Image: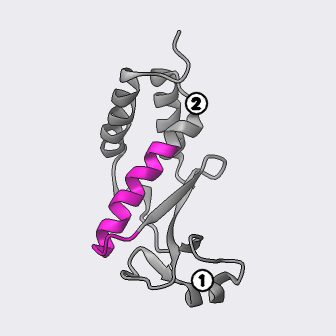
Amino acid sequence: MNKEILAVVEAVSNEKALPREKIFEALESALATATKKKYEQEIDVRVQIDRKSGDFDTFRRWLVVDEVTQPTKEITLEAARYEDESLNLGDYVEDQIESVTFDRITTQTAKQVIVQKVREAERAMLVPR
């Protein structure tokens, strides 16, 4: 439970006037982006954050492939069946992978990614005025 993560969301929500959920979305995109960096295998990783607890877990996903050309971001159909027979060609598999503690990095690093997400919103907003 990282309280700093929940504290940074309150400063970005009032400063960006955006919903806290949206902020966590950008934070997850930054963690996953850096998360896959550790593997260096260009793997698709998704991280979910919990506002109540104040912590996020890193997760990895794969696409069902009949001839997976790269298992770093694609899962074979047979493998998908093992993880979930309900999976088929074109489906996505979910898996939990090691995660990095938020304390490992300072909130200033996330402040840079938060600005990029808000900078793109300046071009246009879903609800102008």
Q: Main secondary structure of the magenta part?
A: helix
Query: As displayed, is residue 90 above or below residue 33?
Result: below
Whole-angstrom CA distance, mark 2 to mark 1, is: 35 Å
The residue nearer to you, when weighing 48 against 92, is 92
Tell me the residue at 72%/78% (across/down): 86
Front tag of 2 and 1: 1
Magenta segment includes 41: yes
Query: As displayed, is residue 31 above or below residue 98?
Result: above
Contact (Cβ within 8 Å) of mark 2 with mark 1: no
The residue nearer to you, when weighing 10 against 115, is 115
Q: Position of residue 116 (x, y in %)?
A: 32, 35
Left/right placement of residue 123 relative to residue 59 reads left
Circle 1 packing at 10 Å, graded few (<14), some (14-19), many (20+), is many
Q: Position of residue 61 (x, y in %)?
A: 51, 70
Q: Which residues are magenta?
A: 25-43
Left/right placement of residue 23 relative to residue 43 reads right
Q: Position of residue 30 (x, y in %)?
A: 38, 51
Mark 1 residue element:
helix
The single residue placed furthest to the right in the displayed view is: 86
If you read the primary sequence from the N terminus, does the residue marked by circle 2 or circle 1 appear first?
2
Say which amino acid is labelled 2. Answer: Pro
Magenta segment includes 36: yes
Q: Which image quarter: residue 78?
A: bottom right
Query: As displayed, is residue 26 above or below residue 68?
Result: above
Q: Which mark is residue 19?
A: 2
What is the quadrant of the N terminus in the image?
A: bottom right
Q: Which mark is residue 126?
A: none
Tell me the residue at 30%/45% (across/down): 109
Q: Which mark is residue 80?
A: 1
